[PDB]
């Protein structure tokens, strides 16, 4: 209009998603009013900002249009060439004129504003309010469940209309070892007709997918214990997705009561895709033979997943006719406290310019080629309990129960070869405020064998990459020990050289061939070539840092970045292993729990450097109360344990860890 | 700040004050003479491709400028200008030229 | 079982063991007694002398029947009502009528007419003689005591811990212990897993779905047992804490720390009315042991948890947070600052050092089962005579930090010339008009005059600030000076 | 078969040729410098 006003434009820089590069270190900064300022620089694979910046512009409603905030995302690192990851140059006049004079929970597409059909390079989550002298908008919403949709959830300055999506075809075959959730009332009703009571009140299970603001549902089964579907449900979403992770939240039908969820899980989209490319231009070290971090075979791909078993978790497996006080565990909130079923499916992705929803019936070929991927092996788990202290409010004798997936649960069994539980004992007062268990020289042990598919050909890689990360992490502590000693830079370089010798030595550790496995898919072809690609990448980073010399801050950045990758490269989305969950009980009442991955105690005959860091080592663990976030003023218990895990063929090797 | 060790022996006399100042605490107004000689190598600040420099001084709560006393479109302009400005200290001690 | 043999013969294994050394390495201990009283729902409170219980509801003797253990002396000649707990003004907790379960779970510090049971806590402090802990080894050699027999009129039910003339039957629990065959080693435990699930054959009165692989218990338990431990000598040096959050409404605290260990807990001297409390205290711990082979045990020390509490008239209910520290083999451990965290919320730091000196002589223990112990020999190396100089005392049996660990001290004078303040911005254009000059460090403070209008005069009428304190001459032991 | 430099790791064919006139380009390679 013709009436200039002091408009305060508030823009918040919140977080990035699905961006190219590794351990990227973007900074967003805008100057104004003759002042010089700097903003915090945020580093990580998926960097967070959480910073608000604003400016006061004395323009009319039709003039503030031409004075946008010059948001840029500049990636600045000391070990490699800096880059612009995208910038935003849209007008701010449209937002003021529109109702509320603001947008909430929207993302900015990151790209070159004047590059037509460039494609997204990831998205930046922001909020924007334009506050005139007579206007207010201090209230904002960032609810993460609302901006999942990739359509009209963002602002497009680059590629104003040129978005490209994909069709994600989910081939869902079957589920096994499901918990009973069917309303227990049927147990009392069926008796009216002379039917026997039971604990097998079967639900009416079906396949449901909810992602990117859209949901699909197909054929519903009834009163079924071990459901088979063979259905292909395709959900459209953006190829450069605005979601970092996909949620699996399936609501089973219940013929007796309201439909509900047996279990939930999440799958990271950063583990099965590379929309920003698989190759970063970050060849740390003195060698850059491909003008890229290393030589890749794929250099980017659509999200994809081979046939694999999905481990779902939620509230306790015990069947009841009462409302579940921990229902949220089955709604995708936090993490579950019990294993609640195994689900197998695969993903095929098509790249398209349009979104569509379709359901297809699978051919026999998709079933037979998947059924032949089914295999089972005997696994060996050992755990010893050395001590337990800092107990509070102990009313009765304490027992713990630990199980793997659906195996070792004392309430789901009548007879098992070994206990998952131990003898009940009373806690003893410490003379001040706490009680402890009088175990003395007796250190309780649990040994269990779960049965599941053989993925050891991928596991060795995980411990290989972690083992390298662990040896490199030690490099950081040693230089800091020298730093407090007021050592010279030359002394730091000496430590770097010593570290480098170990860093390159670890690069001699051979990679497993994962193409031999009959269940291997194109994703495993991706994993193998990416693993050889990144294995050479660390090999290239090695040695070169010994040849040169640097101040400590540079040496620290090198290890920190490589450590992020070495750990990230140990990631495997195809996890067919159920975790280990331990509960502390008072009598038979649950008090506190913890969830343990077995890969850190896992052993392989291939070598010590293919073993988990805690394999055969003493560990200190803590349990947390139901729906606990912090230990607070008092935590359940502090326990000292030793764990070992491996294949039954590794039995002979356990002894060195005993 | 002066931080120093003393002997634990109680027979040792205490140290004197290390520093003293004139109690010029109040509004010690001072006359400021700004001598502007010349400038060179100045960048263009707008689409016209030219720059027409002048000095604006923020002194405390007051603003001083001579925007209409300049030489247009000159690469290395000579000023030779003097500003007779008042200043109350330490209230207007912050002079941004 | 497959891959396994018997470790020894059958031994008596009571359902619970009540024989424990609760004084092991303890110099101080606080005892408590639970006095219960009951009433009719339509009546008033009555007292019974046999209504004293433990935390588990078990019968115990009256508070006045408790005698001093050997090597100890009472600090409290009589039991006092414990008002340092969540109890009412009379020291009682109250509960609703107890059901046939006879196991009250609901207790509050309030009396209600529908409450028919109440419990009072008594508090009595005891401290050890500053001499020897030999009394602990003389009476605690046994892992467990008693024949394990319980008496009943009929076997299988209604058992009692005391004999009655009607008790025609007695019962005691026996346990067996297995050891892995050396042909497979400890790994033999996996020769049982997945194997014994198919092993069971009942052709007699002994009939169980879990027979052979286990008896009595639905599933056979497993454990590692040691006949020895690795002994250590521990000393905790608590010098000073800084920047502690206040828990009291009056912005002060009366902090004391509890040194939390696997089977030990000791209380430090409480420091009153300060958020930068100085202890200069040492706590001495004896017979600290870690189980396992010394070759790897020495490299894997336990975490030590230091829990600070703000003392108050109702007890130190306002827990200030816990700190994690580690000892070394240094004979005079260097002090360092460690964080105190409550609920994952850091609340300050403590300057302290700790030692865990390796003892050559192992702790001696017995493995359950009728076997000859592997640790048939004892290495009689000095128990505590090769230790570094022990701390000086400030009070009877109250130790200070050794001067060898303490920093050498200096008198420090901090002379500040506070000319004026700048960059005072606009705090309501009023509350920054008369800022004060105050200096605090280590609980020591400097006060000065306040000028009503420093907006037109940023300088002070009085610019003198002076502090004189004793500081550490050692930078590591000398905290950043605060202002 | 001619391949484009496509983004996201793809290597599509831009186009190809079919030459049935290949005999028409026959020449003597050693009639020149070699």
Image (tube, coloured by chain):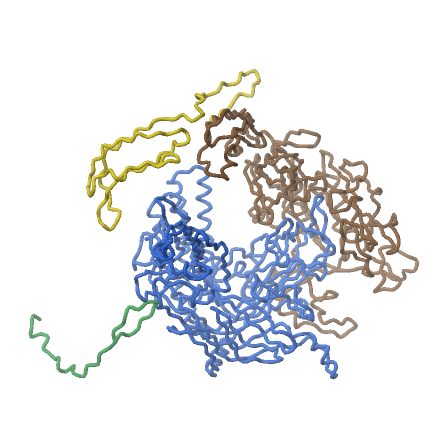
User: Vertical placement of A91 versus A232: above or below?
Assistant: above
Q: Residue at x 46, y 78 (%)?
A: A358
| Chain B shade in the render | yellow
Q: Colour of chain D?
A: green
Residue A629 x %, y %: 59, 55
Residue occupying the point 56% across, 80% down: A220
Instruction: Please tell me whether residue C226 is drawn above or below residue A578 in the rendered image.
Output: above
Residue C187 lies, in percent from the top left, at 59, 62
**In the picture provided, is A592 more to the left or to the right than A169?**
right
Which chain identifier belongs to the blue chain? A
Residue A559 at least partly seen: no
Q: Is residue C151 above or below residue C19?
A: below
Q: Is residue A443 left or right of residue D12?
A: right
The answer to which image quadrant residue C360 occupies is: top right
- Which quadrant is the N terminus of chain A positioned in? bottom left
Q: Residue furthest front?
A: A2
Work out which quarter of the rendered image holds the C terminus of chain A and state it: bottom right
Q: Is residue C176 visible?
A: yes
- Chain letter for the part of the structure drawn in brown: C
Which image quadrant for residue C153? Answer: bottom right
Q: Looking at the picture, how far across and down is residue B37, in whole percent? A: 23, 33
**A180 to the left or right of A284:** right
Q: Residue at x 82, y 43 (%)?
A: C63
């Amino acid at each position: 209009s013709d009436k200039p006003q002091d408009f305060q434009i508030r823009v918040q820089v919140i977080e990035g998603r699905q961006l190219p590069g590794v351990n990227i270190k973007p900074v967003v900064k805008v100057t104004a009013a003759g002042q010089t300022k700097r903003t915090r620089i945020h580093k990580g694979n998926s960097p967070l900002f959480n910073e608000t910046l604003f400016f006061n512009l004395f323009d009319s409603p039709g003039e503030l249009f031409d004075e946008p905030i010059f948001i840029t995302v500049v990636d600045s690192r000391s070990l490699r060439t800096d880059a612009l990851l995208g910038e935003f140059r849209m007008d701010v006049g449209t937002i003021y004129r529109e109702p509320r004079h603001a947008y909430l929970r929207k993302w900015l597409l990151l790209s070159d504003p004047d590059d037509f059909s460039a494609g997204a390079r990831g998205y930046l989550k922001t909020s924007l309010c334009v506050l005139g002298p007579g206007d207010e908008a201090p209230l904002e919403r960032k609810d993460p469940s609302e901006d999942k949709e990739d359509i009209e959830s963002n602002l497009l300055r680059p590629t104003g209309v040129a978005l490209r999506g994909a069709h994600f075809c989910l081939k869902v075959f079957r589920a096994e070892d499901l918990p009973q959730m069917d309303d227990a009332v049927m147990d009392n009703v069926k008796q009216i007709f002379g039917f026997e009571s039971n604990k097998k009140n079967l639900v009416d299970p079906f396949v449901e997918v909810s992602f990117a603001g859209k949901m699909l549902c197909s054929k519903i089964l009834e009163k079924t214990a071990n459901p088979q579907w063979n259905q292909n449900i395709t959900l459209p979403a953006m190829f450069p997705s605005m979601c970092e992770k996909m949620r699996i939240r399936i609501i089973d039908w219940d013929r007796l009561t309201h439909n509900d969820i047996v279990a939930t899980t999440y799958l990271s989209m950063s583990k099965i895709s590379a929309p920003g490319g698989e190759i970063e231009e970050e060849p740390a070290g003195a060698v850059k033979p491909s003008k890229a971090s290393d030589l890749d075979d794929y250099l980017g791909f659509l999200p994809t997943f081979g046939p694999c078993y999905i481990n779902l978790y939620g509230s306790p497996r015990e069947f009841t006719g009462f409302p579940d006080p921990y229902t949220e565990l089955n709604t995708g909130k936090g993490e579950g406290v019990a294993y609640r079923g195994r689900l197998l499916l695969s993903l095929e992705t098509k790249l398209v310019e349009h979104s569509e929803q379709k359901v297809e019936d699978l051919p026999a070929d998709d079933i037979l080629r998947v059924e032949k991927y089914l295999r089972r092996r005997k696994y060996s788990l050992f755990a010893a309990f050395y001590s337990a202290t800092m107990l509070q409010d102990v009313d009765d004798a304490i027992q713990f129960e630990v199980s793997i997936g659906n195996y070792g649960n004392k309430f789901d069994m009548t007879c098992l070869p070994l206990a998952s539980t131990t003898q009940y004992s009373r806690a003893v007062f410490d003379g001040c405020h706490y009680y402890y268990l009088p175990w003395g020289n007796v250190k309780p042990v649990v040994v269990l064998s779960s049965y599941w598919e053989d993925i050891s050909h991928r596991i060795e890689t995980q411990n290989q990459l972690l083992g390298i990360a662990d040896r490199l992490e030690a490099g950081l502590e040693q230089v800091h020990l020298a730093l407090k000693a007021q050592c010279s830079t030359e002394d730091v370089d000496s430590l770097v050289a010593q570290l480098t010798d170990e860093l390159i030595a670890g690069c001699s550790q051979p990679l497993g061939d994962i193409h031999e496995t009959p269940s291997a898919t194109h994703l495993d072809q991706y994993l193998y070539q990416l693993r050889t690609h990144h294995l050479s990448q660390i090999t290239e980073a090695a040695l070169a840092l010994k040849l040169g010399h640097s101040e400590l801050p540079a040496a620290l950045e090198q290890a920190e970045d490589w450590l992020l990758r070495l750990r990230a490269l140990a990631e495997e989305p195809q996890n067919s292993l159920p975790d280990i969950v331990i509960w502390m009980l008072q009598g038979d009442k649950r008090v506190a729990y913890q969830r343990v991955p077995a890969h850190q105690v896992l052993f392989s005959r291939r070598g010590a450097n293919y073993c988990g860091k805690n394999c055969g080592k003493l560990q200190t663990i803590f349990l947390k109360y139901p729906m606990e976030k912090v230990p607070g003023a008092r935590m359940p218990v502090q326990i000292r344990v030793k764990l070992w895990f491996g294949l039954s063929v590794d039995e002979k090797e356990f002894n060195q860890f005993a | 700040f002066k931080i120093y060790p003393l002997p634990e022996d109680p027979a040792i006399p205490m140290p004197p004050r290390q520093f003293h100042q004139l109690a010029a605490q109040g509004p010690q107004e001072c006359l400021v003479r700004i001598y502007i000689v010349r400038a060179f190598g100045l960048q263009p600040k707008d689409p016209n491709g030219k720059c027409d420099p002048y000095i604006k001084i923020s002194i405390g709560k007051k603003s001083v400028s001579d925007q209409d006393n300049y030489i247009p479109c000159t690469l290395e302009p000579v000023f030779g200008k003097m500003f007779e400005l008042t200043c109350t200290l330490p209230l207007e001690k912050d002079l941004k030229i | 079982s497959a891959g396994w043999t018997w470790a020894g013969d059958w031994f008596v294994c009571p359902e619970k063991t009540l024989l424990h050394d609760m004084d092991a390495g303890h110099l101080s201990f606080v005892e408590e007694v639970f006095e219960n009283q009951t009433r009719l729902p339509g009546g008033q409170w009555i007292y019974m002398s046999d209504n004293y219980t433990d935390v588990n509801g078990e019968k115990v003797l009256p508070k006045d029947d408790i005698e001093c253990p050997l090597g100890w002396k009472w600090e409290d000649e009589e039991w006092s009502t414990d008002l340092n707990r969540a109890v009412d003004e009379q020291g009682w907790e109250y509960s609703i009528t107890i059901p046939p379960e006879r196991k009250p779970k609901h207790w509050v510090p309030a009396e209600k007419m529908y409450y028919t049971h109440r419990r009072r806590r008594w508090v009595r402090l005891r401290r050890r003689d500053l001499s020897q802990m030999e009394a602990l080894k003389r009476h605690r050699q046994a892992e467990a005591e008693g024949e394990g027999w319980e008496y009943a009129s009929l076997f299988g039910w209604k058992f009692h811990l005391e004999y009655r003339k009607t008790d025609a039957f007695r019962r005691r629990r026996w346990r067996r212990r297995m050891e892995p065959l050396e042909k497979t080693g400890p790994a033999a435990v996996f020769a049982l897993e997945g194997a014994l699930g198919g092993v069971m054959d009942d052709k007699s009165e002994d009939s169980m779905s879990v027979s052979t692989l286990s008896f009595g218990v639905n599933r056979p338990t497993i454990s590692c047992i040691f006949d020895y431990g690795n002994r250590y000598h521990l000393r905790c040096y608590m010098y000073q804490a800084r920047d502690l959050a206040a828990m009291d409404k009056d912005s002060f605290s009366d902090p004391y720390a509890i040194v939390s260990f696997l089977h030990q807990s000791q209380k430090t001297v409480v420091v009153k009315n300060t958020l930068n409390p100085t202890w200069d205290q040492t706590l001495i711990f004896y017979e600290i042991e870690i189980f396992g082979e010394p070759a790897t045990v020495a490299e894997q020390p336990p975490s030590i948890v230091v829990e600070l509490y703000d003392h108050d008239t109702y007890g130190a209910d306002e827990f200030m947070g816990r700190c994690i520290c580690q000892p070394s083999l240094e004979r005079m451990p260097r002090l360092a600052w460690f964080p105190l965290t409550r609920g994952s919320q850091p609340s300050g730091e403590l300057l302290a050092s700790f030692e865990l000196i390796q003892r050559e002589k192992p702790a001696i223990h017995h493995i359950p089962g009728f076997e000859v112990q592997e640790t048939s020999r004892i290495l009689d190396e000095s128990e505590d005579t090769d230790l570094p100089y022990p701390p000086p005392q400030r009070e009877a049996n109250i130790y200070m930090v050794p001067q060898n660990i303490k920093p050498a001290l200096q008198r420090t004078a901090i002379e500040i010339l506070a000319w004026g303040l700048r960059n005072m911005k606009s705090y309501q254009l009023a509350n920054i008009s008369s800022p004060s000059l105050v200096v605090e460090c280590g609980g020591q403070t400097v006060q000065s005059c306040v000028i009503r209008n420093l907006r037109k005069n940023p300088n002070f009428d009085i610019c003198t600030l002076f502090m004189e304190v004793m500081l550490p001459r050692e930078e590591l032991y000398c905290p950043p000076i605060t202002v | 078969k001619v391949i484009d430099n496509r983004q996201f790791g793809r290597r599509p064919v831009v186009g190809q040729c079919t030459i049935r006139s290949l005999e028409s380009f026959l020449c003597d390679p050693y009639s020149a410098e070699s």
